[PDB]
Length: 286
Length: 24
Image 1 (tube, each protein chain N blue to C red):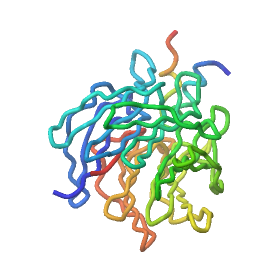
Image 2: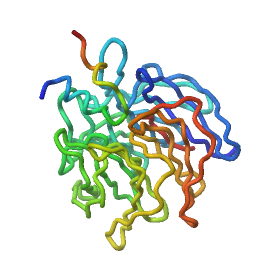
Image 3: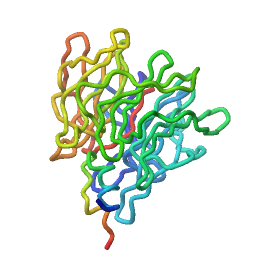
Image 4: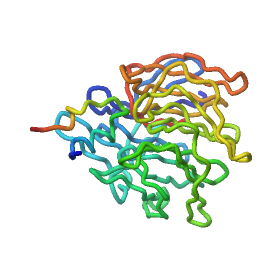
């Protein structure tokens, strides 16, 4: 009956179509309706109890086609529906929700690494561009806290980034925040107890296990306990006050590992694994 | 610095192989 963690898409041998739901109360997994088009490097989010899958790329034996798609999944009917596509394809997109609107941040289309950002209004089924980031970012992690949206890390097409910036929707303005301690592309970014977390990622050479968090009051990033496994392109979400990380690539393997961070004890637990290893998933909870 | 290298570097941290981006 409780909230489930949804994982959509991803990569193992080619881009994937899986939608599976995880119940952290017992570690069980439920396979649901496949996405209509495989994609890796997508994002997931939830608005009004509906799951959305946004952007990515279909890496298949035929091509490497970037996605502009937005698809909506209804857990009560187990059906995927197409929504309006974005202005441009966005592989390695970041997504956050403010007041019921979905913001699509950065990502790539062919050789283009975007700084542009657009927002979707579910009640009108429309996307419109808003102000661009100060930095081109793909592989960027996004989280929203008290109606400010953070874009953390990523890759600008030449440099992996430690920098981060914040969007102020009432001013349609982006402003740089303090940079992270570590360069991270493909990290998992989320918010928990008024801190923005960046877990794992890739610094240009190594997949990382380290985790740091940005305290909005102090404006400082501080390391917390490292995950049990190094990973980039991991899914991440918060469920019942704990962070969950799912899958990723560790420089050797496609992980099926899921771990759960308890912020009181500052510890990571190995919980029940994915049904198969994969990286570049979209995740959300409801 | 060619287009295969640029596309692959967008997914290198998923663990995707460069070979996946090269079609003859």
